[PDB]
Image: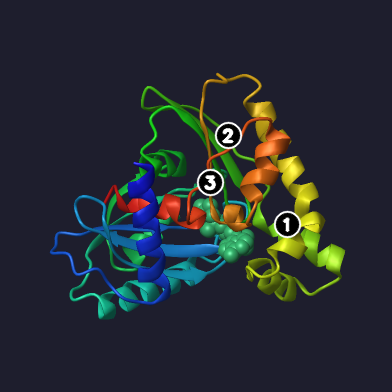
Amino acid sequence: NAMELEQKLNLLNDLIVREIVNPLPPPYKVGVDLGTADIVLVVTDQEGIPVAGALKWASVVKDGLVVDYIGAIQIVRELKAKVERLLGSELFQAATAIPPGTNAEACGHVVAGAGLELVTLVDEPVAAARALGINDGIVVDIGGGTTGIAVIEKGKITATFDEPTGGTHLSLVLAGSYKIPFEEAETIKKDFSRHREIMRVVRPVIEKMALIVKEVIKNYDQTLPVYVVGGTAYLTGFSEEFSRFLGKEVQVPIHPLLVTPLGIALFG
Ligand SMILES: Nc1ncnc2c1ncn2[C@@H]1O[C@H](COP(=O)(O)OP(=O)(O)OP(=O)(O)O)[C@@H](O)[C@H]1O
C-alpha cells in the first residue's frame, strides 16, 4: 500500500500541475474536496487510479461556513470544465466532503450547482483513511484553516475531533515574524527553497499543533499508528519537527495535500 499510495499521489500531482490526463477507459469516479485554502476536483478509474484533476486556491470555507457559496460553484464549475476539456468526455456526478466544524450540506449543493449529481457525502476522516488504506490508526488532517483529528479502528471512525489551527497561522506567524504582507508570506512559505530558512520561525506553531494532538491521543490507544496528511505537511522536515513534539514519529505521505481529495473520489 505505501508504494501504491505514493505512486498514485505523484501521478495525481502531475495530472493536476502539468494539466494532462491518464487515458484510462471509463466509468470514472469523481470527487470534490471543499476546503479552507483550496478546492480540488479529482477523477479516477473504478480501481482508484488517478485519471484527472484540478485545483483552485480558494477560501470558500472560513470556520466551516461556506462563506462564498457562489464563489464555490464558480470554482467547481471552472474545474469541471478544465478537466473536461483535458479529458476526453464530460462528468455527470461526484462525491463530496462535508468538512467537520460547520447546516453545511450546501456542500452537496455546490456539487449539484456545478452540474454534478451528488453521489454521496463523505466525512474527511472517512476519506483520508481510505486513501491511506489504513484500517486502524490516527489521522491528522492538517488543513489550511482547521486541523481535524480522528481515530479509526477495526475499520470505523470510532472517535473524531477538530481544532481551529492550520497552515494559515503558520503563514500568519511567519507574516508577523518576517513583517510581510500575508500574500507575500504565503508565496514564501510555499516556495520549497525557503523551507530551510522559514523553519525556526514557524516551528512554535508546530509545537502547539503536536501537543494538541498529544492531548487528544492522551485518551486513546498508543499502539495506534499516526498519519499526518493535508497541505500543511508540505513543509520539508515537518514530519521530523512534528514527530518530536508529539512524542512518536509520524507518517506523512509524498503529496500530503492530495490524500483526502483522492479519498473522496474513491466514493463517487
Ligand atoms: N509547498 C508547500 N509548502 C508548505 N505549505 C503548503 C505547500 N502547498 C500547500 N501548502 C499549505 O497547505 C494548506 C492547505 O492545505 P489543505 O489543502 O489540506 O487544506 P484545505 O483545502 O484548506 O482543507 P482540507 O484539509 O480539507 O483540504 C495551505 O496553508 C497551504 O499553504
Q: Residue at x 18, y 76 (%)?
A: 88
- Residue 174 lies, with reference to residue 191, above or below; the image says above
- Residue 234 lies, with reference to residue 52, above or below; the image says above
Q: Residues within 10 Å of mark 3 (few under 14, many from 20)?
A: many
Viewer-side label of 1, 3:
3
Question: Looking at the picture, which amino acid does disc 2 mark?
Answer: Phe
Q: Residue at x 63, y 57 (%)?
A: 235
Does residue 188 appear in this view? yes
Mark found first going from the N terminus, 3 or 2 = 2
- Which of 29 and 118 lies nearest the eye of the viewer? 29
Q: Give me the disc on residue 252.
A: 3
Q: Residue furthest bottom?
A: 85
Q: Which residue is mark 1?
A: 170
Q: Position of residue 183 (x, y in %)?
A: 70, 74
Question: Looking at the picture, which amino acid does disc 3 mark?
Answer: Val
Question: Looking at the picture, which amino acid does disc 1 mark?
Answer: Leu
Is residue 26 left or right of 111 when viewed as pictured?
Answer: left
Q: Residue at x 48, y 57 (%)?
A: 255
Q: Position of residue 190 (x, y in %)?
A: 63, 68
**Is the shortest distance between ligand 1 and the CB of mark 1 under 8 Å?**
yes
Q: Position of residue 158 (x, y in %)?
A: 46, 24
When asked about the image quadrant of residue 141, the answer is: top right
- Residue 152 lies, with reference to residue 164, above or below; the image says above
When asked about the image quadrant of residue 176, the answer is: bottom right
The N terminus sits in image quarter: top left
What is the C-alpha distance between the residues marked 1 and 3? 18 Å
Viewer-side label of 3, 2:
3
